[PDB]
Image (cartoon, rainbow, N blue to C red):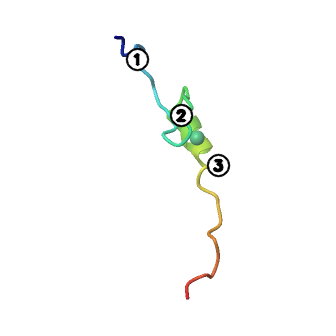
């Protein structure tokens, strides 16, 4: 009977997308860019 969880060590920032920690908030924002850059399926509408 053990939860087996963890979480001891405050963090500056984390990419909710993938989960990458960055020293500066600027470095993180610049990274997230990779997450925001995909094209939609297409014209498929009807
Ligand atoms: Zn990311």
Residue 21 horizontal/vertical position (percent): 54, 28
Residue 34 badge:
3
The answer for how far apart the CA atoms under marks 3 and 1 are is 30 Å
Task: Name the secondary structure under disc 2.
Answer: loop
Find ligand 1 in the image and state its quadrant.
Answer: top right
Residue 3 horizontal/vertical position (percent): 36, 16
Pair 3/1: label in front: 1
* Residue 29, image quadrant: top right
Pick whichever of labels 3 and 2 is earlier in the sequence: 2
| Residue at the image point whose x is 64% and y is 48% from the top | 34
| Residue at the image point whose x is 63% and y is 71% from the top | 41
* Residue 10, image quadrant: top left
Pair 3/2: label in front: 2
**Residue 38 or residue 1, whichever sits in front:** 1
Residue with the mark numbered 1: 5
Q: Residues within 10 Å of mark 1 (few under 14, many from 20)?
A: few
**Residue 3 or residue 15, whichever sits in front:** 3
For label 3, being within 8 Å of ligand 1 is answered yes
Residue 6 horizontal/vertical position (percent): 42, 16
């Amino acid at each position: 009977g053990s939860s087996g969880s963890s979480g001891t060590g405050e963090n500056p920032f984390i990419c909710s997308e993938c989960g990458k920690v960055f020293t500066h908030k600027t470095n993180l924002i610049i990274h997230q860019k990779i997450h925001t850059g995909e094209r939609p399926s297409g014209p498929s509408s009807g």
